[PDB]
Length: 94
Length: 97
Length: 241
Length: 50
Image (cartoon, rainbow over all chains, first blue to last red; front, side):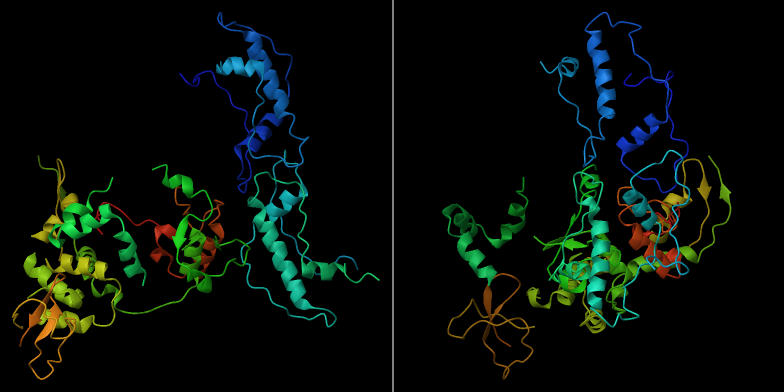
């Protein structure tokens, strides 16, 4: 399936006010900011095909680039990732 | 006095979220969007020293430049007003000896 | 004047002139047809998706009392907020001739409110188009009655649009009461009760009898009037009393 | 959803909300307003042909 069904959990935003209408990116940022407990990630079940360090570096990259918006004076509406080796391998650009 | 005391009201935001900490400009915009009932403004007491149409144009420009945020690909943090003739007269930028 | 110059520059090309000169007006319809939703909910999210005429600038203000723009300049581009503003506070015309041709709908409503349903059981054209033409299109009648007089009397100078009035009159002039509510009375395994409750032509166009004239020639001009006139929408013929 | 035409007495915030609110507050008989501009829906099985 495209998305898993029985094993999913949600990071809620705890009853936003009735006047809250906005961009999904900032909603996701707010939902992520309400959670504490991140640790050093590591692999538990390999894919037995492909490179797993690319996946780990992709997760680290998405975390870092989600945490790196405050350096901009003109914060955007959409987020574009940086074309790196791990993402190029994962998306099958070659 | 710098700000009037007895004759002031407020436009409450009605209990923002406990995790909400943002720029005051967006808070002001969200406070403004909660009011309906704007009409055509008009002078009720002249200043008897100056030009009142400049005040009308300043208020209208404030409203227009607050509404025209959406015409931007990137959302700004602070608002810089356009240097207009009425604003220049109000700020006294041409009366420098 | 654009009409004549479009005629002039349209026939400059030989390919577009042979077609216009060879085929006749009898073959108009057979050549008109030779032409070669997420789309709707994608241009409504962008500003100014509607087309209007230039006169909207004089009547509708550019900005509202809040500060939102209503139209922009380069037939100009406008937003639905302009339509809502017009519906809110605009010029008002209280003419009674709007339903002058819409009754054929109204009795339907009159046949719906004034009715009783009761219990339910679970048992297991030319003769009209000719008058339409003489009523709506006096200047384009063919080479051919109390209803005609009544229609000309009741809607003489209060027209809205020729196409809409023509369609409505055709629908009105051309049992049905039980058929029109077939979706409510009859079902797949149930039935619901319900009660509603002239001149003559001597020949072709003649250049000696001056220029041609229009159809509106009630003034016979001494009853002779051997006059060239455009009959129907085709050629010019001579007319005698 | 597609034509941004919600009821006048709703909290949904769109670009057409202000004009719809003003029109809703201006009128007296609110049942005669079209669905296109902040109006109620009166359609049912019996009204499908009008």
